[PDB]
Image (cartoon, helix red, strand yellow):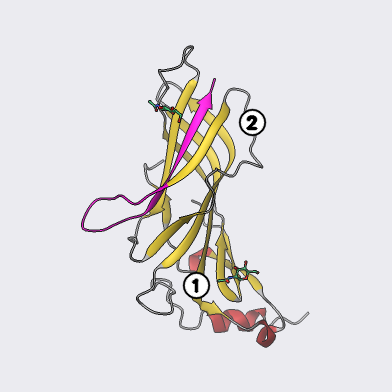
Amino acid sequence: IAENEDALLRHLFQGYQKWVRPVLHSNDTIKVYFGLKISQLVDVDEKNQLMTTNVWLKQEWTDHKLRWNPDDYGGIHSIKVPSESLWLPDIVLFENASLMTKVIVKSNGTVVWTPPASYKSSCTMDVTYFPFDRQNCSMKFGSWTYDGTMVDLILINENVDRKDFFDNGEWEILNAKGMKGNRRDGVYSYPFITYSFVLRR
Ligand SMILES: *[C@@H]1O[C@H](CO)[C@@H](O)[C@H](O)[C@H]1NC(C)=O
Ligand SMILES: *[C@@H]1O[C@H](CO)[C@@H](O)[C@H](O)[C@H]1NC(C)=O
């Protein structure tokens, strides 16, 4: 086989600077579509009010530097590229608790990144219900480096993605909904997404 896959890569990352936002015009914000997918609830530590989860952080955005006509490159329309090479919006889980997988890049600039993660975030037993088999657990995600001027978050679904979720014997997910906030400290606006989990038993 003969791969102009190597030519596209050399042409795509020639003078690429992963630290410059890959916008066309410098006035532009980069829109990052975001969604949380849960694989399983690993453990609910009722003592320390903590929760550990296995999740994927679904991210998608446009990198206007990484755009090509497939006709020039043997009809390639998509390629897999290491996340370490790309500009990233640097979305993190806020209350410290995102492995560097590879990214998919498409000839129109769309980048799809879904890195897996394992987190231990804080919980809160619901005292309104007796017996006490409810817990309120929140996960808050947003860019660390870029304010809303430079990265805007778009929440792709009101619900956490659970199609591939593993029900663990000991707790059940009553609800898991995401909502957008735009609140952070300083003379800067920072958009974020809060996911609220209601766990039973
Ligand atoms: C690029 O093409 C894909 C289909 O492969 C599509 O899902 C995506 O919306 C396109 N990107 C843009 C920025 O239109
Ligand atoms: C816990 O979550 C439930 C469901 O969203 C809500 O009705 C309740 O007000 C919350 N209370 C606390 C203390 O978290």
Judging from the image, what secondary structure is the residue with disc 1 in?
A: strand
Q: Is residue 28 above or below residue 133?
A: below
37 or 157, which is in the foreground? 157
Q: Which residue is mark 1?
A: 63
Judging from the image, what secondary structure is the residue with disc 2 in?
A: loop
Q: Residue at x 39, y 68 (%)?
A: 29
Q: Residue at x 64, y 71 (%)?
A: 79
174 or 96, which is in the foreground? 174
Q: Residue at x 37, y 46 (%)?
A: 94
Q: Residue at x 75, y 82 (%)?
A: 2
| Residue extending furthest toward the top | 131
Residue 183 colored in magenta in the image: yes
Mark positioned earlier in the residue sequence (2 or 1) = 1
Q: Which residue is mark 2?
A: 167
Q: What's under tag 1, amino acid-wise?
A: Asp
Q: Which mark is residue 44?
A: none
Q: What segment carries the magenta color? A: 180-201
Quarter of the picture containing the N terminus is bottom right
Measured as percent of width and height from the top left, residue 149 is found at: 33, 65
Badge 1: residue crowd in 10 Å (few <14, some 14–19, many ≥20)? many
Q: What's under tag 2, amino acid-wise?
A: Asp
Measured as percent of width and height from the top left, residue 24 is found at: 43, 79
